[PDB]
Image (cartoon, coloured by chain):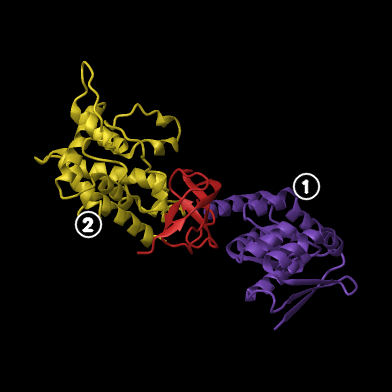
Amino acid sequence: TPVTLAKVIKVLGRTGSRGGVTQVRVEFLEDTSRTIVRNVKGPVRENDILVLMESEREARRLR
Amino acid sequence: FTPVVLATPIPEEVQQAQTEIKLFNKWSFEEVEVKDASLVDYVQVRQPIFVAHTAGRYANKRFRKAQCPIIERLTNSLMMNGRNNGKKLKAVRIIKHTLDIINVLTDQNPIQVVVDAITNTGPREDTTRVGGGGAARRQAVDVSPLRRVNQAIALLTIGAREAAFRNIKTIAETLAEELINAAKGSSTSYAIKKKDELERVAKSNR
Amino acid sequence: KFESRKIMVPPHRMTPLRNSWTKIYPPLVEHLKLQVRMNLKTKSVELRTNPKFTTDPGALQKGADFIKAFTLGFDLDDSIALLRLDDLYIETFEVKDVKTLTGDHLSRAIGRIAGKDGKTKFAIENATRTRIVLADSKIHILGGFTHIRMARESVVSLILGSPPGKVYGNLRTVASRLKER
């Protein structure tokens, strides 16, 4: 199974109608040349570590 | 181990177990294994406690929560149903019983079994109910490691309590049962079920 | 293995060009890896891609679209936004296209699009996430297709001599039904 490892490097803020999901810029761990735009449902800090499945998916803005 | 005789002497089994560098009476934290890098620093428990009963004031800082013992954390997440609220002695004894079962379940390291359960039962990616205009579709998010561990311990304790209700089995046996069906995920546990379904609807919704 | 696109610079827009140039060519040559020559005599910007520049086909095109976007009197920031995003395009209408207007009738018409202290144009953009340029008889729009369609709608409604209020109504109607979605 494809377990992608992520590294929350930059916190962008909070989105969603409810205002809960964090917009986050991710430095890929295994291949450090990939920087993904990811959404997180949970409390995140800087230099964190996520576990994604589709590293080629990006997220502009949330309603 | 060089024993010491006082006037009122400490029982020999205590002295022996703790001067043999054993952190409980039947277990040790020096043998604990984490699989992902995301769980390493959010599950971390390297201080030996004999009771899994700490006056933790970690509810004052959000990340500070991740430095409170995971066995004490699963212990306080046992205490969920409204009738058992405000009873930590019950949960601690029950966890000690569970550990007495995972040993006699042909598993040499109950602590690594639990940690591997926590590693296996935390959902990688999830969904959120984002607007989209009335008919709210579900955006595939990627849940945090902190909430991964949270949701893990949650699904575990809840599945186990939901199983141990209205059946003769004691809570420790369905908690060991859950933690072992989830230690190495078998799709016979509640937590692996729900994790796989959350990641499945997260997959279908992207 | 080269490629050469050459775009003419209008006289009017040239002075701000040689004003902000130093902020202009670096994101091209450095962020996109491209050759940006400038003939100040023949008023032309020259965008070349060469083999020593990495392989990205639409990069050069995107360059020329930056340049033409700024050429049309748009701002730097919005043109850089053009480099970044693909979904952003540029519409153009004449006023004579929608309704044949003579003299002062044309003049006033323009005002109905601008409004006192730009207030009306502002309103249209912010509710349609776009950038508008009010040239002479030409109007230019910059943004997403689904957006610039709406922008064209309300601006046309203005050019037909409909009162600004009505257009505000349609505007918040559309902005609501789209920001909702």
The picture places residue B61, in percent across and down from the top left corner, at 45, 33
Image quarter (top left, top right, bottom left or bottom right) of the N terminus of chain C:
bottom right
The picture places residue A19, in percent across and down from the top left corner, at 48, 43
The secondary element bearing badge 1 is classed as: helix
Left of A46 or right of it: where is C13?
right
Looking at this rendering, what residue extends furthest in the front direction? B2
Looking at this rendering, what residue extends furthest in the left direction? B168
Q: Residue at x 67, y 70 (%)?
A: C62
Front residue (pair C137, C122): C122
Q: Residue at x 17, y 45 (%)?
A: B103
Residue C156 seen in the figure:
no
Q: How many discs appear? A: 2
Residue A12 seen in the figure:
yes
Image chain in purple: C
Front residue (pair C25, C159): C25
Above or below residue B187? Residue B86 is: above
Image chain in yellow: B
Q: Which residue is mark 2?
A: B186
What amino acid is found at the position of numbered circle 1 in the picture? Asp
The picture places residue B145, in percent across and down from the top left corner, at 41, 48
Determine the chain carrying the residue at label 1: C
For the residues labelled 2 and 1, the Cα–Cα distance comes to 68 Å
Disc 2 versus disc 1: nearer the observer? 2
Left of C144 or right of it: where is B79?
left
Q: Residue at x 43, y 45 (%)?
A: A42
Looking at this rendering, what residue extends furthest in the right direction? C41
Above or below residue B38? Residue A31 is: below
Image chain in red: A
Above or below residue B17? Residue B115 is: below
Above or below residue B92? Residue B35 is: below
Front residue (pair B181, C148): B181
Q: Which mark is residue C117?
A: 1
